[PDB]
Amino acid sequence: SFSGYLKLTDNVYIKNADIVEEAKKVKPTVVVNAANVYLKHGGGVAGALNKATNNAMQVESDDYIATNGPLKVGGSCVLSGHNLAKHCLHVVGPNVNKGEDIQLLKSAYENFNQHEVLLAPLLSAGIFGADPIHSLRVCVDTVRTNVYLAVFDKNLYDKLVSSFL
Ligand SMILES: CNC(=O)Cn1cnc2ccccc21
């Protein structure tokens, strides 16, 4: 199972780790992707997860979009986890760099409640432009299922733990 995680609450855990390396080691039932509405996995967590699948995640995602159209900001879809997990829960957090509504972050975290345990990044953090301290607060106040957060950046991980209320 998951190892080396710091317990924040009854159900939220955090570790300074590369989510791709974490997924390969654990092979969780669900890995969460920080997706956009088009499932275009170009950069950040999405680009890294997709590259680990040798682009199989993008091929599957393009077929999903051709059939279903784009996701909503705050929405999600369950696709294959490929070599990383049983499933990948593609969750769209608001991208504040694309002028999207930050109040949608709670809606985005609500998707995690449909899965008993997940390996996840902080939604809307990184290249999505939101404050990761705010994202962690929304996560612990929204997610009731067991979420193992992988924070890539060591300095951000320390800031998150040392400032956690
Ligand atoms: C093998 N893994 C990678 O390519 C590392 N990597 C790149 N962007 C990232 C963003 C978040 C976490 C890990 C990330």
Image (cartoon, rainbow, N blue to C red):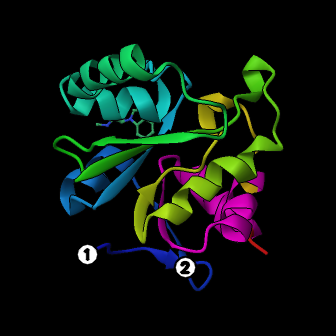
Question: Looking at the image, which is closer to me, 47 or 64?
Answer: 64
Which residue type carries mark 2? Asn
Magenta-drawn stretch contains 159? yes
Depicted 120 relative to depicted 80: above or below: below
- The answer to whether residue 50 is left or right of residue 146 is left
Q: Is residue 18 visible?
A: no
Q: At 61% from the left edge and 36% from the top edge, which residue is drawn?
A: 126
* Residue situated furthest bottom in the rendering: 10
Q: Secondary structure at mark 2?
A: loop
What residue is shown with label 1? 1
In which quarter of the view is residue 116 placed?
bottom left
| Residue 119 place in picture, x, y as percent | 40, 59
Q: Secondary structure at mark 1?
A: loop
Magenta-drawn stretch contains 89? no
| Residue 147 place in picture, x, y as percent | 49, 67
Which residue type carries mark 1? Ser
| Residue 98 place in picture, x, y as percent | 74, 18
What residue is shown with label 2? 11
Q: Is mark 1 within 8 Å of ligand 1?
A: no
